[PDB]
Amino acid sequence: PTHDVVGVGFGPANLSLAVALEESPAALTSAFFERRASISWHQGMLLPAAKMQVSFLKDLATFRNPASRFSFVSFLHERGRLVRFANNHDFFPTRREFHDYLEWAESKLAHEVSYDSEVTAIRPGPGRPVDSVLVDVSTPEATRTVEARNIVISTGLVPRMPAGVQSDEFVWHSSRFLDHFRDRDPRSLRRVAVAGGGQSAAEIVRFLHDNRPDTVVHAIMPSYGYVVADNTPFANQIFDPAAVDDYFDGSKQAKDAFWRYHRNTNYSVVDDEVIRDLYRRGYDDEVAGAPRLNFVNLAHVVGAKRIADDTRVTVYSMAREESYDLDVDVLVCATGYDPMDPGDLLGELAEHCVQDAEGRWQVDRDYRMVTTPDLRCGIYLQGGTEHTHGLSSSLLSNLATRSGEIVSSIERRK
Amino acid sequence: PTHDVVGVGFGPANLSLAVALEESPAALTSAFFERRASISWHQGMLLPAAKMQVSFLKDLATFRNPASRFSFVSFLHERGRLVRFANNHDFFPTRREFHDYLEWAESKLAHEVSYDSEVTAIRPGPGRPVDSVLVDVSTPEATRTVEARNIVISTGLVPRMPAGVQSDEFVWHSSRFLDHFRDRDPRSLRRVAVAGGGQSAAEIVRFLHDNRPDTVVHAIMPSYGYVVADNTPFANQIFDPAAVDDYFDGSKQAKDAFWRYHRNTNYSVVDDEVIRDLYRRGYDDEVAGAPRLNFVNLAHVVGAKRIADDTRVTVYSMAREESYDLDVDVLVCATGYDPMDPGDLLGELAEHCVQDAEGRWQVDRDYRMVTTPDLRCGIYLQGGTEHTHGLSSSLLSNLATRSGEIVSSIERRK
Amino acid sequence: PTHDVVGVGFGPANLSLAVALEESPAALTSAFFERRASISWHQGMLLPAAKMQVSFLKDLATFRNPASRFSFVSFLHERGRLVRFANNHDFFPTRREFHDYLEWAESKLAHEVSYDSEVTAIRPGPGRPVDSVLVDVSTPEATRTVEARNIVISTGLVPRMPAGVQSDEFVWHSSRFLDHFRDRDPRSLRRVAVAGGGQSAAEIVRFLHDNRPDTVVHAIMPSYGYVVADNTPFANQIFDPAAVDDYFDGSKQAKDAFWRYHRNTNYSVVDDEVIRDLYRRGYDDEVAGAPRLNFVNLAHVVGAKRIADDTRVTVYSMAREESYDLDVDVLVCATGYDPMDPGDLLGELAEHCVQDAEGRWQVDRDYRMVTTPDLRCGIYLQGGTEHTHGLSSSLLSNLATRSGEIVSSIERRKS
Amino acid sequence: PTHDVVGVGFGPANLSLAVALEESPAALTSAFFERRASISWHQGMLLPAAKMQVSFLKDLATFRNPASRFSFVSFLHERGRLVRFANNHDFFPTRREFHDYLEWAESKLAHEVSYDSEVTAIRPGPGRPVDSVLVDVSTPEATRTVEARNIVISTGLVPRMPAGVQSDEFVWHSSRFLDHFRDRDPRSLRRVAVAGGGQSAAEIVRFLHDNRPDTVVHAIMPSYGYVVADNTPFANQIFDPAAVDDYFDGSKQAKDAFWRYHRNTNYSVVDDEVIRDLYRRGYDDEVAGAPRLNFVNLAHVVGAKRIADDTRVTVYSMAREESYDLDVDVLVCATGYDPMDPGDLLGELAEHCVQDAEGRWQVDRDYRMVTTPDLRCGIYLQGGTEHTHGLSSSLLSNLATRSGEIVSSIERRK
Ligand SMILES: Cc1cc2c(cc1C)N(C[C@H](O)[C@H](O)[C@H](O)COP(=O)(O)OP(=O)(O)OC[C@H]1O[C@@H](n3cnc4c(N)ncnc43)[C@H](O)[C@@H]1O)c1[nH]c(=O)[nH]c(=O)c1N2
Ligand SMILES: Cc1cc2c(cc1C)N(C[C@H](O)[C@H](O)[C@H](O)COP(=O)(O)OP(=O)(O)OC[C@H]1O[C@@H](n3cnc4c(N)ncnc43)[C@H](O)[C@@H]1O)c1[nH]c(=O)[nH]c(=O)c1N2
Ligand SMILES: Cc1cc2c(cc1C)N(C[C@H](O)[C@H](O)[C@H](O)COP(=O)(O)OP(=O)(O)OC[C@H]1O[C@@H](n3cnc4c(N)ncnc43)[C@H](O)[C@@H]1O)c1[nH]c(=O)[nH]c(=O)c1N2
Ligand SMILES: Cc1cc2c(cc1C)N(C[C@H](O)[C@H](O)[C@H](O)COP(=O)(O)OP(=O)(O)OC[C@H]1O[C@@H](n3cnc4c(N)ncnc43)[C@H](O)[C@@H]1O)c1[nH]c(=O)[nH]c(=O)c1N2
Ligand SMILES: NC(=O)c1ccc[n+]([C@@H]2O[C@H](COP(=O)([O-])OP(=O)(O)OC[C@H]3O[C@@H](n4cnc5c(N)ncnc54)[C@H](OP(=O)(O)O)[C@@H]3O)[C@@H](O)[C@H]2O)c1
Ligand SMILES: NC(=O)c1ccc[n+]([C@@H]2O[C@H](COP(=O)([O-])OP(=O)(O)OC[C@H]3O[C@@H](n4cnc5c(N)ncnc54)[C@H](OP(=O)(O)O)[C@@H]3O)[C@@H](O)[C@H]2O)c1
Ligand SMILES: NC(=O)c1ccc[n+]([C@@H]2O[C@H](COP(=O)([O-])OP(=O)(O)OC[C@H]3O[C@@H](n4cnc5c(N)ncnc54)[C@H](OP(=O)(O)O)[C@@H]3O)[C@@H](O)[C@H]2O)c1
Ligand SMILES: [Br-]
Ligand SMILES: [Br-]
Ligand SMILES: [Br-]
Ligand SMILES: [Br-]
Ligand SMILES: [Br-]
Ligand SMILES: [Br-]
Ligand SMILES: [Br-]
Ligand SMILES: [Br-]
Ligand SMILES: [Br-]
Ligand SMILES: [Br-]
Ligand SMILES: [Br-]
Ligand SMILES: [Br-]
Ligand SMILES: [Br-]
Ligand SMILES: [Br-]
Ligand SMILES: [Br-]
Ligand SMILES: [Br-]
Ligand SMILES: [Br-]
Ligand SMILES: [Br-]
Ligand SMILES: [Br-]
Ligand SMILES: [Br-]
Ligand SMILES: [Br-]
Ligand SMILES: [Br-]
Ligand SMILES: [Br-]
Ligand SMILES: [Br-]
Ligand SMILES: [Br-]
Ligand SMILES: [Br-]
Ligand SMILES: [Br-]
Ligand SMILES: [Br-]
Ligand SMILES: [Br-]
Ligand SMILES: [Br-]
Ligand SMILES: [Br-]
């Protein structure tokens, strides 16, 4: 049995794809595979006060269909919270609530996702021309293979550690913060270093300050202070559906300009309110004569070693041009992520995929990889399109339209 | 041809009723009569910067049906302004845009509304007990009559002038502000008095200040300064549909408590931002050495007379306990409105309508007037229920649910 | 040794006064008596996040002297926090910081305040007409009497419990919340009722929510929800120095209008940010499926009794018009305060103080009590002037000007 | 008569110097020369709604002396506007008010500034080593020379036009906008192009939009939309006096990091409120069906020519890598400024001043130019220290401390 489309991974991107498929009048068969036991949307960073970075209007479907049964508003309504929510006058739900929104949408779906199912490889199906791919799925029981005309790869961002630093028992990447943190002894983390100057770093430092009154925190970052995230209406336009076209059709020079001027809409920056809350906390501690937040500015973490009961963090100071050591209990690296890269999954097929001069994957406007003529199957990317489609690639800004264009593309070809 | 329901007036309340009728699976016949040529939603006060006092989520239908084709979001989408709107991160549309929303919703409707049609009386149909009512409609050419099993009266708020003051060519009620203003010679309104301390008074003063750089304005109000409108999330819960119950089922003592603590949510109060804008304007004028805004606090307007080229306003000062005259070109009375009273329209029918101890109409929870067995046809009120249903009666807070409850009620009895 | 002026109590008002005395070129002798061991400014309510309700510009002196050594700005500078503070862009200091500001100002003063000194009575001095008063001061060791040509009474607001409810081991007035709370065992305050819909009530409920995540709280108040405090610029003008004139010279009618329209600038109301924080808290608990905040609206606490291990709170519901019992661990009554009353302290001198029709003290514009000719000794009130001077009387809005006007009055009358 | 110190220019920087001199117990003689007839602080850009970018606490003296007779608070008090101002709860005065503050401070000063006096050169005084400088001052009547042991150069930012574009009758630099705007006839500026994406460009566009209702405006800028200014509390720390030290003592690596991460605090960025107001204006025009603001993003102005009665602006589009002509009435170039150059008055003395490797003036922390032993007189810079002291140089953030440090330095060496 050969499916019209198979989705690899089940985060928000393929969820919105599933929703788009259901709402389309086109009769398309599909299967989705998620390695984890259920939807798990950055649970390691589901901190108490964490808030979405996208407006509730930017949900699974609303921008494409303003009367979707899968809209965030529909979800508030069935939960009996729409009125309460509207009273609050906040365009930004909590991460906690949005996570519930995802699970609610998944349940509503007619079709069933296959959990505990890791896709291990994608191989060319039989014959010429190649009209199908073979998808190798590993369950905890048994391995198997499914066949599909089209495949949609949406496996998410990949944690990135500082060069020369490896994750270990007392060294964590931010993505795994709560998983480690909930599993400690509550008074065996009196000294924590957090590396990074982005949203993750800021939220973790905030949480630590708010959690235990006696934790001392070292916030280590290359800038002189947190840099504000730009979420003013015009800059935010780069996430408009039409701005995808502008980036896509634009020259390399124009693409560079988007990054030069507007990377501060998302990368290595912190939300205004979180910055102000941290600043207020620092100020009040100073007034109380009990400083706890140590901001190590203009600096990078360059190494970590466990020495007896201490995690020894090597810090490079850009001001002094020298390195030194800080001793803590745990090092949290909030040092960001690498883009989704379909390559590692593609091993058979990658040689049917065209690269550009700088060796990156060519991708069509409709998120479809560029292939050899012998490949006729569709390979679509949700994620990993930073270089072709722009800053919206890893974000929640454009779920409805992106998923819709992919579904239309697939239909247009069947 | 006897209609299931006839709507008198076509403002937002009956519009939402029309929408509720179309979305209901119940097959109900209806007709709507509006005395004006088209939807005309306080156009006299459609000032340049005027904002809705209610969230865009509080539209014609969303609270009842979160995926209505008549939602504000659907409107934005069809106009191609949903993305732009979301980027603004403002819950409050402009009055101008909301007016366009109403006209858009009216056009989408399958039913056609009858314009230029004034309802002049409502009479008992032929029968005992009465199973229908007759509805007299006057058009420019003819007069006719319509028979209905239910009526819904939604005529509006009635302009109220100060005691002992009659409107005039030089003495305007705020409701007609732009009708008189528009084409009045600019060089002829150098001195304007505005009576009142509410949202209407504040917006008019602001507009005058913004629009002619030489007008001198006297803002006359009983308070020592504008009182802020309470729109904090808890107080705003009095407009929750569950709060309608809470008022309705509550004792007279409880009802009085709503008004004594929370009338500040709507009556005789001014929006925070409008207050601050006025204050900023006054401050800057002082800095510039050119005061323009004269605030006559602890005061009321008690009379007006035209004397040669001057409108002479008699002001009573509470502080001094005396009266004095103030000469201006025009007096604008932003002195508020009276609730909608169905009584005039009913005439003949009033007698089968039950009153309470204090002489007020009794109304069931579903907005249906209490009648004597002599009457079995339904008379519903959208407006004029301040005493029975509470502060939401004249407002836009609860359109979707009240219209829905009325439609359900009519279907239930049929 | 007869002093020109004696101050009873040493809160911000009398501190203000001490500052005004020092800055005045007039050579006036003065003594201040405070019952407590040191300045103690509503310490029972010094909660972690508590913020001033008045701008830092409304400090001890700035409105009268823009370049005072006692300004809040000066304080920030000396503490090396002025630059940091400026960057925060908030006009409202924390209560904790403001408390440090007061202590700092007191230390800088050339005068020394007598602490642990309770004023127990004020008596007519010798002779007629009375040219001085005698101030009875009780210390832990001894008792003594001092003599003064003028006296300034500034003893502060007085806690007010609900009628028919008495403070106790398990029934606290908000003013003493942290006093009691810091003593009790955490696992023993699982159930708390808080009565009131004002700033105190709201702050206490937020603190409980934020500081113990398994505490259940019942917020009992007469309104349908918290009412917002009006702090918009025009309404705030009622606290302007000139508005004190406007209230004072105005008829009863106009005085009543101030209260009818603008009592919501201060009484029985809650700051916008605190309301939204509480609302956010409730919302997030509902999402998590773990409700903890129970808002009991349109209601009054009418009684409390201890029954075994439970504090039984009798609540009257206005909606239903019945009463019922609610069991908790502690009842906190955030039910407000009564105005300062110079009455009790005055005793005999009250005979020489003139009352109005409704039996209240007559007070001149300069805060001096109206007296018969048999008394020429100045009695000034900082507090307790709500009926003559208006809503600024118990607040921090007008410290600089009021203190300055009292000092000027005293000096104008010395000669 | 040899002065201890001579100030060239009398803007806020030297004004704070004059104040610092008067408050210092040191008896130092001084003279100040200003080319203009009076204090003239960017009057070309004194637009109606223009706000300070710096807090009122950052005034001429307060950070140094919290109880200065020259504080902004003292100013408000004398003008009887301290109470009113505090009620507003806005840290940012208007530019108009601040200008009045300057003039007020200048009048209070005991010292008398010499206006209409343009410094044309600074030359070494007699014999070696030079112990004084000679300052050539040109008045409308005559030219004279004064002698001084120290000199403070504070001549301000220098307007910078685009490469290939010259100011003219219909091509204006933003600095002269009001001077130019005012003579013109309203009916003659129906089409205006404004180049730039910074605070100047944004304010000018907003003013045009607000001041005429028919003007069509082309906003031409290299970014995809306005970039928000970073004004969050850690970011404002860059301007702390203690941060001057951090920048000064830091390596060249560290210095680069300040600019890389935090130039957005000031350069090529727009205040949050101004951005939202422009966005609101664009939105309402679209609703009204009358678009007037044309945002020409990802673009540069590269030439201008007058052709009959139009100004032909050549625009380069990065997106299309192409240029085209845009015809208008006036081109306003809001393309920024070039930092103060100590060097152009310096002439011969420049031989005795030390450059570094990249050819830049060496400057001591106390703002004094590094000289050979042949020069012993002090040359101080307020402005032109971007390289050595950082982003605070042209700004108002640090007037009190900078002026105080310079006064102390001069006293110390005397
Ligand atoms: C803490 C935090 C918070 C946010 C964000 C990031 C982070 C780190 N983001 C960005 C983030 O990229 C976005 O929110 C989504 O996670 C993107 O959804 P995806 O479907 O692309 O992948 P997603 O990252 O959700 O995961 C895809 C799934 O594929 C699975 N998978 C991987 N390999 C597989 C295999 N071989 N076989 C089967 N399954 C496999 C993974 O297990 C995973 O569940 C964000 N952006 C924004 O615009 N607004 C926001 O609020 C946030 N919030
Ligand atoms: C300037 C201004 C602005 C606002 C508001 C009021 C005012 C004065 N309001 C309140 C206002 O009542 C509400 O917005 C609606 O107008 C109420 O709808 P009805 O449909 O109930 O009245 P209206 O909307 O007043 O409906 C009445 C209609 O009936 C017609 N009519 C009257 N008599 C008739 C007859 N005999 N025969 C036929 N037709 C007849 C009238 O022509 C009119 O069109 C408000 N509230 C809120 O919550 N948010 C807001 O933003 C605003 N905005
Ligand atoms: C929790 C809280 C918080 C605030 C406020 C109230 C409360 C309850 N207030 C109002 C308050 O009234 C004001 O801040 C000061 O307390 C008033 O100064 P007095 O100096 O008038 O009172 P207090 O400040 O009450 O001064 C009275 C002193 O006299 C002493 N005393 C009493 N009897 C004595 C005796 N017989 N002998 C000697 N000493 C005696 C007392 O011990 C006390 O120290 C306020 N207002 C505002 O405008 N902004 C704000 O931010 C706040 N904050
Ligand atoms: C529209 C606008 C608005 C602002 C700002 C810039 C602009 C363009 N700035 C930055 C600006 O640099 C600052 O406000 C001051 O103008 C700097 O003072 P100087 O005293 O340093 O320059 P400034 O230009 O003010 O003074 C220079 C003076 O020297 C005179 N002069 C030059 N050469 C001379 C000679 N040879 N002989 C005699 N006189 C001579 C000039 O005539 C001029 O009066 C700012 N920054 C900030 O932090 N917050 C803010 O709000 C603003 N606002
Ligand atoms: N509440 C939410 O919804 C939420 C929460 C967290 C994250 N997110 C999202 O997750 C995505 C990624 O955010 P992120 O914060 O996790 O990463 P970033 O990629 O946004 O964070 C990286 C930061 O660490 C710094 N860094 C790199 N190497 C370092 C080193 N050796 N030592 C110290 N610091 C170092 C970076 O500096 P430089 O880049 O300058 O070199 C940068 O400041 C974003 O889209 C973000 O919005 C969302
Ligand atoms: N951060 C700060 O600076 C801070 C903090 C706390 C307080 N304060 C100040 O101190 C002053 C007083 O504030 P406050 O909140 O302490 O007291 P408050 O303003 O007088 O409020 C008292 C409240 O209790 C209610 N109440 C009275 N009896 C009740 C009963 N039997 N049951 C339930 N509720 C009852 C009152 O309702 P009704 O009046 O409607 O009947 C009112 O809501 C104010 O000036 C205030 O701003 C300042
Ligand atoms: N209210 C106030 O107090 C106020 C008002 C105005 C200005 N200021 C201050 O004055 C200083 C300068 O502000 P500013 O806006 O005038 O200067 P600016 O910050 O340098 O802004 C210059 C802008 O023009 C752009 N640009 C340069 N060449 C261009 C070209 N050929 N075509 C199109 N665009 C071009 C720049 O782009 P790129 O940088 O990307 O190259 C930049 O966006 C700041 O300190 C500022 O805050 C204050
Ligand atoms: Br948290
Ligand atoms: Br968004
Ligand atoms: Br709901
Ligand atoms: Br890890
Ligand atoms: Br483009
Ligand atoms: Br689509
Ligand atoms: Br609302
Ligand atoms: Br759209
Ligand atoms: Br009228
Ligand atoms: Br307007
Ligand atoms: Br008048
Ligand atoms: Br009269
Ligand atoms: Br209802
Ligand atoms: Br319903
Ligand atoms: Br707290
Ligand atoms: Br205030
Ligand atoms: Br400081
Ligand atoms: Br107690
Ligand atoms: Br008055
Ligand atoms: Br005074
Ligand atoms: Br000279
Ligand atoms: Br600032
Ligand atoms: Br003043
Ligand atoms: Br030209
Ligand atoms: Br020019
Ligand atoms: Br303007
Ligand atoms: Br550093
Ligand atoms: Br740079
Ligand atoms: Br163009
Ligand atoms: Br400095
Ligand atoms: Br200094």
Image (cartoon, coloured by chain):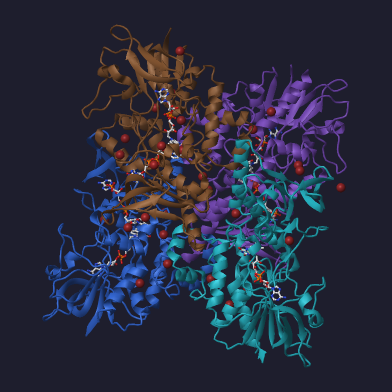
Chain colours: A blue, B cyan, C purple, D brown
Q: Residue at x 59, y 26 (%)?
A: C68
Q: Position of residue B209 (x, y in %)?
A: 63, 48
Q: Quadrant of residue A100?
A: bottom left
Which one is nearer the viewer's eye here, C200 or D187?
D187
Relative to A355, D259 lies left or right: right
- Residue C229 appears in the rendering: no
**D82 vs D414: above or below:** below
Q: Position of residue B243 (x, y in %)?
A: 63, 68
Q: Quadrant of residue A49?
A: bottom left
Which one is nearer the viewer's eye here, B164 or C256?
B164
Image label count = 0
Which one is nearer the viewer's eye here, D299 or A255?
D299
Relative to A364, A353 lies left or right: left
Which one is nearer the viewer's eye here, D262 or C47?
D262
Displayed-image quarter of ligand 26: top right
Q: Quadrant of residue A43?
A: bottom left
- Residue B52 appears in the rendering: yes
**B371 vs B298: above or below:** below
Q: Position of residue C136 (x, y in %)?
A: 75, 27
Quadrant for the C terminus of chain B in the image: bottom right
Quadrant for the N terminus of chain B in the image: bottom right
Q: Position of residue B376 (x, y in %)?
A: 73, 88
